Amino acid sequence: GPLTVPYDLPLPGGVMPRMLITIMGTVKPNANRIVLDFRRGNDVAFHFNPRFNENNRRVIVCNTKQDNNWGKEERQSAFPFESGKPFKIQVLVEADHFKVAVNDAHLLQYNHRMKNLREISQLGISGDITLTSANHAMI
Ligand SMILES: CO[C@@H]1[C@@H](n2cc(-c3cc(F)c(F)c(F)c3)nn2)[C@@H](O)[C@@H](CO)O[C@H]1S[C@@H]1COC[C@H](n2cc(-c3cncnc3)nn2)[C@H]1O
Image (cartoon, rainbow, N blue to C red; front, side):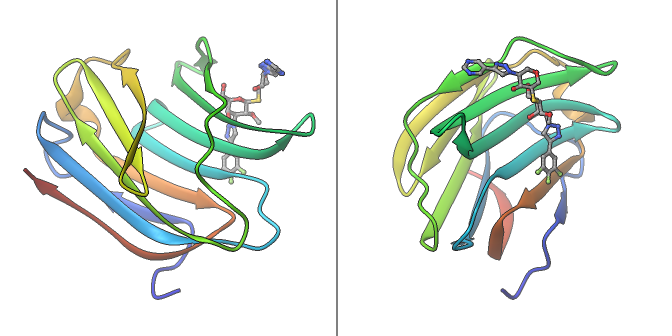
């Protein structure tokens, strides 16, 4: 697609409430996973990881990695992605959580574990996708 995967979207000044990140693309026909990683260097404040075939099930895993410890996984069985199909992911930053919507439907909320939001300066987009667009705006 017009953007190369993996793709790093800089977040100058980090994330702040009211920030909306929009990502559009298509899932590859033989997809295994998608990853969105809100990063503070080597740490990952918010890892959003649709897994298409984990023990023969679809699941979204969300987590945080701080000092190479992954935390408690937050798992959602609701899974709005499909092999070969277009998607739109929107992540809205609020003061207490990230809110994620896919295809204009609310999917999940993830409470901030890494709380220095102005230091989360990169969003990495990786995995089995074609990416058409990735951008952010303050709403
Ligand atoms: C492979 O390690 C993944 C982590 N990961 C994935 C990637 C990644 C990055 C990229 F750039 C990529 F391109 C890319 F493809 C993947 N980087 N780190 C990350 O997703 C992390 C999130 O917690 O998970 C580990 S695997 C983690 C291992 O520990 C046990 C966990 N396990 C199994 C079950 C469980 C619970 N309920 C029902 N069935 C099974 N529960 N926990 C398991 O999920």
